[PDB]
Image: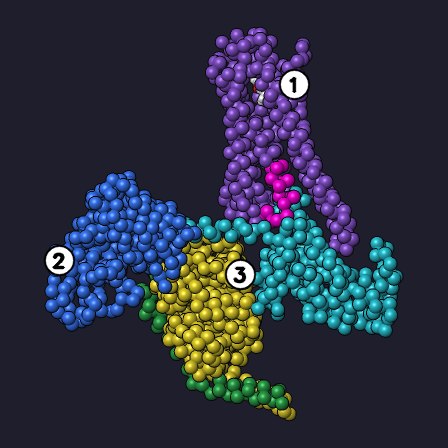
Chain colours: A yellow, B purple, C cyan, D green, E blue
C-alpha cells in the first residue's frame, strides 16, 4: 500500500503507454522506406585545418552566418575562427580551464561557455572598447554544466550535472524556470527550430521533451541501454536523434511517441560523442571514440562514409546553417572543415 | 697523375680483376643493397605514419638518411676501385674519398645526437610528448654542417698533394695529420656516448633501488634493468665492433714504421659501413609501432 | 587579397604569438587530481565547482585539483597522477573505500594514470589497535588468521600489533592494483598523519618516478 | 510523506504523458520521407555542389 | 568614455621640425591600428600615415614619405608623428583615427580633435555636387564616383562615408558601402555598385548638415572625396 500502492498505479500506467505505443506501430519506417534510391558513397575531404588550440577541444558551435565559428579547449581559451580564411577573430581567455560546452548567440553579439565551475559565463563580443568582456555569470546550478544554447540575446537554457535543466534571463541574471524529472546527469540539449520546445538526454538512458513556456515535461523516450551522450533535432522539428555509449544512434518521433530507426553496426563497439543532421535531414553525421565520424543514411540506416582525419577522440561536431560544411573537433587540438 | 702518388705510398694499381679483388666486391655489393633497402624503409615509415611525427623520430629519420648516403657513397667507390682506380684524376680522387668522409661523419654525429637527446629526456621531469621541437631542427643542421665541412676540408688546403713528405699509406693523397684528426673525433664521440649511456643506467639504478617494497617489489625492478642493460649494451657493442678495427688501423698508419697496413684496409671498410646496415635495426627493433607499420608497406 | 583582409591576418598572427607565450608557460607544471571521501582528511595532506591549490617543491610547480558515477573523470585524462586519500582509522567504511579504489583503478579513461595512495590518519589507527576495543577481524575475516607481517622492514618503535594492522590494510589496496593494469600504471602506497609535513616531498618523489618510467617506455629504452 | 509526495508527482506525470494524441508510424514514416525528398536539391552535402559556388576550397 | 586627446601644433617656422602626439584613453589602445588624417583650411580630408597594432606595418602618403615618421607607445597609451623639413603646404589640422581590422569590424570609428599646425596609379574619388541647398524634412541623395572598381573578389565593396559637422571632427556613419555604424540611426542608408555609389538620407531632421566625404579602403594610399556641403535654407 501507500507508495507500494502508488507503485502498482505507476506500473499500470507504464504498461498503458507501452500498449498505446505498440498499437500505433502498424509498419516500420525502415520497411516503408525500402523503395527509395540510396544516397551513394559520400566522400568528404578536409578543406581546412584550424590550428592554435594547445589541448583537447571539448565543444564547438557555428555562427548563424555559417562563416564564424567558436571553439573551446582545456587551455582555458575561447577562439573565434573565420572558417574561410582560417583567421582568428578573437581569443577569449577563461577564468576556469575546465570548460565542457560553448555556444554562439543567434544574433552574433554573444558567446557562452561553462563547465566544471558550475557557471555559465556570457561574453560581449561587440564592445566599444574593442575587446571581449564577460557580460554576466549565471550561478545556481549545483552540478557541472554540460550544455548551453541561446534562444535569443536575453534567454539561454543550460543543462547541468545536477539532473536538471534551467532557463535563464540574462538581463536579470536569475533562473526563470527549472526542468526536473531526469534521474541521471543531463549531458546534451537541443533547441527546436521553432524554439517553443527542446529535448535533453541524460545518463539515465532517457530523453525528455520539454515545453519552455509551460516548464514541464511533455514526453519521455526510453530506448537506449547506456548514457545518452549526444542529442540533435531533426530539421523538420518532428523527430530527433540520440547517440549513446552503447555504440548506437536512434531516431525518435515526437508525434508517434515511439522509436523509429536504430543506427548500429557489429564492428562498432565504442561510444558516440556527438551527432548532427544535414540540411535536408537525409544524412546523419555522428562522431565516435574510434577517432573518426560516420555518415548514416537517416532513412535507410546504412553507412555512407567515414570522416577519418583525426588521430584522437572526436569530441564535437557541427553542420552549418546552409549545409555547406561540417566542422569536426577532436582531442588532438585540431578542428577540420569537411566538404 | 694518380699512379705517381700511389708509387711512393707502396700501394698497387690493379690492371685486371684479381681473385682477392672480386672477394671484396662480393660482400661489398651485397652490404650496400641492405643499406639502401633497410634505411629507405625507416624514412618512409615515419612519413606515412602520422603517429611518428615526434622529435625523437626526426633524429631516427635523419640517421636513416645519413646512413642511406653512406651506402650510396660506398656504391660509387666499388665501381671506381680495383681496375677502375687506374684511370682516376686528382680532382676525381679527392671527390671519391671525400664522399665517404662526409657520409661516415654524418653517421657518427647522429649517434651522438640520439645519445644526447635520450640523456635530455630521461633527466627532465616532464613528458617527452609535452616537449618543443626547436631542439631537433637546430641540431640536424649542425650535424650536416660538420659532415660537409669534414668532407670538404681535405679537398682544399689540407691535402698532401702540396707537401708529399707525409702522405698516408692507405689514402695516398691524404695527409697523415688528417687521418689522426679523424681518429680522435670518433674516439671522442664514443667516449662521450659511453659516459652519457652509463649515466642513464646509473640514474635509473639509483631511483629503482630506493623506490618501495610495496609499489611493485623486486619483480618489476629486475625486468627494467634487464631490458635497459640490453639496450645500452647493444648500441655500444655496435659502435665498438664495427669501428674499432677500422679506427686502430688509422692510428697504425701514422707513426708506425714498416707495419702491414695495406692488407687489412680492404675488409675494414666493410666493417665500418656494416654499422650503417644494422644501425636502423638496433634503433627500431624495440618499437612495436615501427615493426607494425613495416608490414603495412611491403 | 585586399588591404582590409591583409590587416586582419596581421591581427590573427599576433594572436598565435600570445597563444604560445602562455602555452609554453603551462608545459612546465604538473597537474594532479585529488580524490577521496569526506572523512578521509582529503584537504589536509599538503599544508600549502572545483577547488585548486598550488605548491612548489624543488622548483617544480604542482597543480592539485579537488572537485567539491563520475562522468567528469574523463576531463582528467592527461593528469600526471591521481591522489587517493583513505581514512584507515575506521573499518566500517574501509570496505566502501576499497570499492572506491576499484572503480578508479579499472576505469576506462584512467588506464595509464598512476595513483599515489595516502592512508591518512595512521595515528588513530595505532590507538585503535593498541588500546583495542575493536577487531578488524569482525569486518575483515581474513585478518583473523592473517599472516603475520611478511618479513620486511618495519618502522622503529611501532608495536608488532600495529605493524600487523598497517601491513594488512596496505595489502588490500595493492591487491587490487596488481590484479590488473598490465604494468601500465603503478600504485604508490603511503602512511600519513594529520601533523605530517613531508607529504609534499612524497608527491614530488612519486611523480618523478611516474614520469621516469613512461619516458623510458615511449622512448623504447626499456 | 516524502515518498508519498514523490510517488504522487511521478503518477501525475505519467498520466499526462499517457493521454496524448499519437499518430500512426506509417504517417510518421511518410512525413520524414516527404521532407527529405522535398529538400534534396537544398542539401550540398548530399548532392555535390560545383566548385565555383564552394566557399571552402 | 573613448577619448583621443591631441597635443602639439601651433605656429612654427618653415623648414623646421615639429612632433605631434595624440593621447588615447577609454579603449584598448594596443589592439587598434591608428591613422593620421589632415584637413587643409580650404579643402577636404587627406590621409597622411598609418601604424598598425604592434607597429608591424607602416604606410605613408607619397607627399610625406621620407620626411614624416609615425610611431606609437603602447605602454604609455599614446602615438607620435615626427614631422621634419616642413613646408608651407603642411598648414592643416591633423586628426588621429583609430581602426581595428577583423571579420565584420568597422574601421575609422573614433576621430579625435585636431591640432592646428601653422607653417609660416592612385584611385581618385569624385563628387560632382559640392553645395546643395536642402530643406528640412525632405530627402536627398549624395553620390560619389571612383576611377577603379572598389568591389573585391571576396564580395566586399570598400567604400566609407563620413560626416563633418561645422566645428566638429568627422564621424563614420556608413562603412563598406552598406553597413550602418553604431549610434547612427536608420535614417541614413548607403547603396551602390561598382564605381557608382550614393548615400540616401530620408526625413532629414536638424543636425544633419555638414560635409559628406566618400573614401576608398581597397588599397593604400586611402583617398577621400572632395565633399558635398549641405546648407540651411
Ligand atoms: C681503414 C679504416 C676505414 C674506416 C675508418 C675511416 C673512414 C674514412 C674516413 C676518414 C679517414 C681518412 C680516409 C681513410 C680511408 C681508408 C679506406 C679507403 O677508402 O681505402 C681506399 C680503398 O677503398 C680503395 O683503394 P684502391 O683500391 O687503391 O682504389
Instruction: Name the residue at 29% across, 67% down.
Output: E183
Q: Can you give x and y, in whole percent of width and height, for residue A101 in the image?
A: 49, 65
Q: Can you give x and y, in whole percent of width and height, for residue E219 in the image?
A: 26, 48
Q: Is mark 1 within 8 Å of ligand 1?
A: no
Q: Which residue is mark 3?
A: A97
Query: Residue B251's mark?
Result: 1
Depth check: give the residue in front, C118 or C15. C15
Q: Find residue B64 and report its image quarter.
A: top right
Q: Secondary structure at mark 2?
A: loop
Depth check: give the residue in front, A149 or A282. A149
Ligand 1's quadrant: top right
Instruction: Name the residue at 50% across, 67% down.
Output: A114
Instruction: Name the residue at 67% across, 37% down.
Output: B197
Q: Can you give x and y, in whole percent of width and height, for residue E93 in the image?
A: 24, 52
Q: Disc 2 versus disc 1: distance between alpha carbons?
A: 95 Å
Q: Which residue is mark 2?
A: E130
| Magenta residues, start to end | B114-129
How packed mark 2 is, by other alpha carbons closer than 10 Å (few <14, some 14-19, many 20 or more), is few
Q: Where A29 falls versus B289 (above or below)?
A: below
Q: Secondary structure at mark 3?
A: loop
Assess whether mark 2 and mark 3 are in contact (beta carbons under 8 angstroms). Answer: no
Residue A41 visible in the shown view: no
Q: Disc 1 versus disc 3: distance between alpha carbons?
A: 63 Å
Depth check: give the residue in front, C170 or C43. C43
Amino acid at each position: 500500500s501507500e507508495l507500494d500502492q502508488l507503485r502498482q498505479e505507476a506500473e499500470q500506467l507504464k504498461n498503458q503507454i507501452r500498449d498505446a505505443r505498440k498499437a500505433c506501430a502498424d509498419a516500420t519506417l525502415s520497411q516503408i522506406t525500402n523503395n527509395i534510391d540510396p544516397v551513394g558513397r559520400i566522400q568528404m575531404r578536409t578543406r581546412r585545418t584550424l590550428r592554435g588550440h594547445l589541448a583537447k577541444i571539448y565543444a564547438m558551435h557555428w555562427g548563424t552566418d555559417s562563416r564564424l565559428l567558436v571553439s573551446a579547449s582545456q587551455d582555458g581559451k575561447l577562439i573565434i575562427w573565420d572558417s574561410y580564411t582560417t583567421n582568428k577573430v578573437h581569443a577569449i581567455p577563461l577564468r576556469s580551464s575546465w570548460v565542457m560546452t560553448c555556444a554562439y548567440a543567434p544574433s552574433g553579439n554573444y558567446v557562452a561557455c561553462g563547465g566544471l565551475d558550475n557557471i555559465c559565463s556570457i561574453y560581449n563580443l561587440k564592445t566599444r572598447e574593442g575587446n571581449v568582456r564577460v557580460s554576466r555569470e549565471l550561478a545556481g546550478h549545483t552540478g557541472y554544466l554540460s550544455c548551453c544554447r541561446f534562444l535569443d540575446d536575453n534567454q539561454i537554457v543550460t543543462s547541468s550535472g545536477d539532473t536538471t535543466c534551467a532557463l535563464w534571463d540574462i538581463e536579470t541574471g536569475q533562473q526563470t524556470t527549472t526542468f526536473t524529472g531526469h534521474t541521471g546527469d543531463v549531458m546534451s540539449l537541443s533547441l527546436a527550430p521553432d524554439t517553443r520546445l527542446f529535448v535533453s538526454g541524460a545518463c539515465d538512458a532517457s530523453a525528455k521533451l520539454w515545453d519552455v513556456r509551460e516548464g514541464m515535461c511533455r514526453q519521455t523516450f526510453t530506448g537506449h541501454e547506456s548514457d545518452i551522450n549526444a542529442i540533435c533535432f531533426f530539421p523538420n522539428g518532428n523527430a530527433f536523434a540520440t547517440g549513446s555509449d552503447d555504440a548506437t544512434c536512434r531516431l525518435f518521433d515526437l508525434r508517434a511517441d515511439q522509436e523509429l530507426m536504430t543506427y548500429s553496426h557489429d564492428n562498432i563497439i565504442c561510444g558516440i560523442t556527438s551527432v548532427s543532421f544535414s540540411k535536408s535531414g537525409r544524412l546523419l553525421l555522428a562522431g565516435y571514440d574510434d577517432f573518426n565520424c560516420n555518415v548514416w543514411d537517416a532513412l535507410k540506416a546504412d553507412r555512407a562514409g567515414v570522416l577519418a582525419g583525426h588521430d584522437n577522440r572526436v569530441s564535437c561536431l557541427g553542420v552549418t546553417d546552409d549545409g555547406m560544411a561540417v566542422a569536426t573537433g577532436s582531442w588532438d587540438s585540431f578542428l577540420k572543415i569537411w566538404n | 697523375s694518380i699512379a705517381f702518388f700511389y708509387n711512393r705510398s707502396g700501394k698497387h694499381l690493379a690492371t685486371e680483376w684479381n681473385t682477392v679483388s672480386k672477394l671484396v666486391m662480393g660482400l661489398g655489393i651485397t652490404v650496400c643493397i641492405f643499406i639502401m633497402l633497410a634505411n629507405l624503409l625507416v624514412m618512409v615509415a615515419i612519413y606515412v605514419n602520422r603517429r611518428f611525427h615526434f622529435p625523437i623520430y626526426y633524429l631516427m629519420a635523419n640517421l636513416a638518411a645519413a646512413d642511406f648516403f653512406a651506402g650510396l657513397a660506398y656504391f660509387y667507390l666499388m665501381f671506381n676501385t680495383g681496375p677502375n682506380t687506374r684511370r682516376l684524376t686528382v680532382s676525381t680522387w679527392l671527390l671519391r674519398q671525400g664522399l665517404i668522409d662526409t657520409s661516415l661523419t654524418a653517421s657518427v654525429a647522429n649517434l651522438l645526437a640520439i645519445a644526447i637527446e635520450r640523456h635530455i629526456t630521461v633527466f627532465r621531469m616532464q613528458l617527452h610528448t609535452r616537449m618543443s621541437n626547436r631542439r631537433v631542427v637546430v641540431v640536424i643542421v649542425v650535424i650536416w654542417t660538420m659532415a660537409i665541412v669534414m668532407g670538404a676540408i681535405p679537398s682544399v688546403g689540407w691535402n698532401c698533394i702540396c707537401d708529399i713528405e707525409n702522405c698516408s699509406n692507405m689514402a695516398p693523397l691524404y695527409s697523415d695529420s688528417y687521418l689522426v684528426f679523424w681518429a680522435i673525433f670518433n674516439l671522442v664521440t664514443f667516449v662521450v656516448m659511453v659516459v652519457l649511456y652509463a649515466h642513464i643506467f646509473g640514474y635509473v639504478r639509483q631511483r629503482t633501488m630506493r623506490m618501495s617494497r610495496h609499489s611493485s617489489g623486486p619483480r618489476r625492478n629486475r625486468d627494467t634493468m634487464m631490458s635497459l642493460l640490453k639496450t645500452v649494451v647493444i648500441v655500444l657493442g655496435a659502435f665498438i665492433i664495427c669501428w674499432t678495427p677500422g679506427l686502430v688501423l688509422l692510428l697504425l698508419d701514422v707513426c708506425c714504421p714498416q707495419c702491414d697496413v695495406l692488407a687489412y684496409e680492404k675488409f675494414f671498410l666493410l666493417l665500418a659501413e656494416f654499422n650503417s646496415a644494422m644501425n636502423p635495426i638496433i634503433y627500431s627493433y624495440r618499437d612495436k609501432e615501427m615493426s607494425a607499420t613495416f608490414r603495412q608497406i611491403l | 587579397v585586399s588591404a582590409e583582409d591583409k590587416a586582419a591576418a596581421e591581427r590573427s598572427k599576433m594572436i598565435d604569438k600570445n597563444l604560445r607565450e602562455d602555452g609554453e608557460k603551462a608545459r612546465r607544471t604538473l597537474r594532479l587530481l585529488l580524490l577521496g571521501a569526506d572523512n578521509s582528511g582529503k584537504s589536509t595532506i599538503v599544508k600549502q565547482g572545483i577547488f585548486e591549490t598550488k605548491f612548489q617543491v624543488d622548483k617544480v610547480n604542482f597543480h592539485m585539483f579537488d572537485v567539491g558515477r563520475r562522468k567528469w573523470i574523463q576531463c582528467f585524462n592527461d593528469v600526471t597522477a591521481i591522489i587517493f586519500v583513505v581514512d584507515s582509522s575506521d573499518y566500517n567504511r574501509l570496505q566502501e573505500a576499497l570499492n572506491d579504489f576499484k572503480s578508479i583503478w579499472n576505469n576506462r579513461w584512467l588506464r595509464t594514470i598512476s595513483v599515489i595512495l595516502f592512508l591518512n590518519k595512521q595515528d588513530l589507527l595505532a590507538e585503535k589497535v593498541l588500546a583495542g576495543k575493536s577487531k578488524i577481524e569482525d569486518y575483515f575475516p581474513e585478518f583473523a588468521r592473517y599472516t603475520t607481517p611478511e618479513d620486511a622492514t618495519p618502522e622503529p618503535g611501532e608495536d608488532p600489533r600495529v605493524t600487523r594492522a598497517k601491513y594488512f590494510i596496505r595489502k588490500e589496496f595493492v591487491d587490487i592494483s596488481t590484479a590488473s593494469g598490465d604494468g601500465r600504471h603503478i600504485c604508490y602506497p603511503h602512511f600519513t598523519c594529520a601533523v605530517d609535513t613531508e607529504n609534499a616531498r612524497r608527491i614530488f618523489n612519486d611523480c618523478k618516478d611516474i614520469i621516469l618510467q613512461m619516458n623510458l617506455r615511449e622512448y623504447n629504452l626499456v | 510523506t516524502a515518498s508519498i509526495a514523490q510517488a504522487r508527482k511521478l503518477v501525475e506525470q505519467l498520466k499526462m504523458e499517457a493521454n496524448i494524441d499519437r499518430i500512426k508510424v506509417s504517417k510518421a514514416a511518410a512525413d520524414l520521407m516527404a521532407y527529405c525528398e522535398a529538400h534534396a536539391k537544398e542539401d550540398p552535402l548530399l548532392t555535390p555542389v560545383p566548385a565555383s559556388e564552394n566557399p571552402f576550397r | 568614455d573613448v577619448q583621443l586627446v591631441e597635443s602639439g601644433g601651433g605656429l612654427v617656422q618653415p623648414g623646421g621640425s615639429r612632433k605631434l602626439s595624440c593621447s588615447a584613453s577609454g579603449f584598448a589602445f594596443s589592439s587598434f591600428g591608428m591613422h593620421w588624417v589632415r584637413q587643409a583650411p580650404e579643402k577636404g580630408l587627406e590621409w597622411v600615415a598609418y601604424i598598425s597594432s604592434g607597429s608591424g606595418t607602416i604606410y605613408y602618403a607619397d607627399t610625406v614619405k621620407g620626411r614624416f615618421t609615425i610611431s606609437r607607445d603602447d605602454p604609455k597609451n599614446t602615438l607620435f608623428l615626427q614631422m621634419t623639413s616642413l613646408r608651407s603646404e603642411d598648414t592643416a589640422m591633423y586628426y588621429c583615427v583609430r581602426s581595428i581590422y577583423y571579420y565584420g569590424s568597422s574601421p575609422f570609428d573614433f576621430w579625435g580633435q585636431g591640432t592646428t599646425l601653422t607653417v609660416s596609379s592612385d584611385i581618385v574619388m569624385t563628387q560632382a555636387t559640392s553645395s546643395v541647398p536642402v530643406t528640412p524634412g525632405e530627402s536627398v541623395s549624395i553620390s560619389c564616383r571612383s576611377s577603379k572598381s572598389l568591389l573585391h573578389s571576396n564580395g566586399n565593396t570598400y567604400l566609407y562615408w563620413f560626416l563633418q559637422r561645422p566645428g566638429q571632427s568627422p564621424q563614420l556613419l556608413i562603412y563598406r558601402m552598406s553597413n550602418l555604424a553604431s549610434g547612427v540611426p536608420d535614417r541614413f542608408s548607403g547603396s551602390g555598385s561598382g564605381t557608382a555609389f550614393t548615400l540616401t538620407i530620408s526625413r532629414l531632421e536638424a543636425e544633419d548638415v555638414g560635409v559628406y566625404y566618400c573614401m576608398q579602403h581597397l588599397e593604400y594610399p586611402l583617398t577621400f572625396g572632395a565633399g558635398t556641403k549641405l546648407e540651411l535654407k
